[PDB]
Length: 172
Length: 90
Ligand SMILES: *[C@@H]1O[C@H](CO)[C@@H](O)[C@H](O)[C@H]1NC(C)=O
Ligand SMILES: *[C@@H]1O[C@H](CO)[C@@H](O)[C@H](O)[C@H]1NC(C)=O
Ligand SMILES: *[C@@H]1O[C@H](CO)[C@@H](O)[C@H](O)[C@H]1NC(C)=O
Ligand SMILES: *[C@@H]1O[C@H](CO)[C@@H](O)[C@H](O)[C@H]1NC(C)=O
Ligand SMILES: *[C@@H]1O[C@H](CO)[C@@H](O)[C@H](O)[C@H]1NC(C)=O
Image (cartoon, rainbow over all chains, first blue to last red; front, side):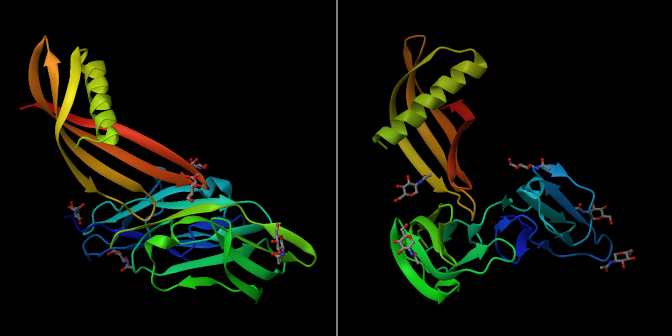
């Protein structure tokens, strides 16, 4: 077991729409002798050396895998970032969960596009409905939560469904 | 140990071994199989430690094979990746 650094996303969504803001933060110890950070994008070292890596407006090139490292923490596992372009996007912090983990999904709309009467669906069957767009929570994840997920709502009178994404729940 | 998924990995291990070392081993059977899941938030992955029997010039010999299987998702497209990382006799 190595003291692996960890990259986490603020906000937590690993699937984002173009122009969204994303800040990547490295969870790792920083010694006073060497307080720099090594960031990697698609396995390649990048120039930024700060503990945080800011993406003001995300573009498709910002997509890919990210890793970080510090003097006291070893190379982290990769974190995946997907930049989507479309009217509607189902968001999640990851697609692999363990039993009892919380599952927090969000139905995100293109910039300046209100959305209402939102439904989260699992394997084609609806799971939760909201008249006003709200997030979907599952505090305790179970093996039955695995499946293909997508959200659909109303842009006024236009009924729209987001692209699907597969979630998997593993043993705890 | 004696399932189809195990055998395919063992045959894959033998096919890859012969390819890189330019050898001619003939798979026979799997005799022991140990699995070690290594998932993350963004991959369903397992490391397989397989002991198999293969014919080396007609003579049966036992080999230990380390096979890495990785499943990732991009948008909604799944990608399966298999890799032989170690192949040694006993
Ligand atoms: C930590 O930084 C020092 C220099 O301040 C360097 O000599 C050392 O190799 C670094 N440790 C690691 C694990 O990179
Ligand atoms: C990192 O170290 C340098 C040189 O010692 C110092 O100038 C800088 O303020 C330090 N940064 C932090 C965040 O402590
Ligand atoms: C990183 O890899 C992803 C995966 O296809 C790609 O979409 C993205 O453009 C890549 N970024 C760079 C800077 O190479
Ligand atoms: C939207 O369309 C789906 C079928 O495409 C339908 O089941 C649903 O009732 C419609 N309205 C809402 C608010 O989902
Ligand atoms: C997503 O999971 C469902 C399980 O009901 C499966 O039928 C479907 O093939 C999966 N999709 C992909 C792309 O693996």
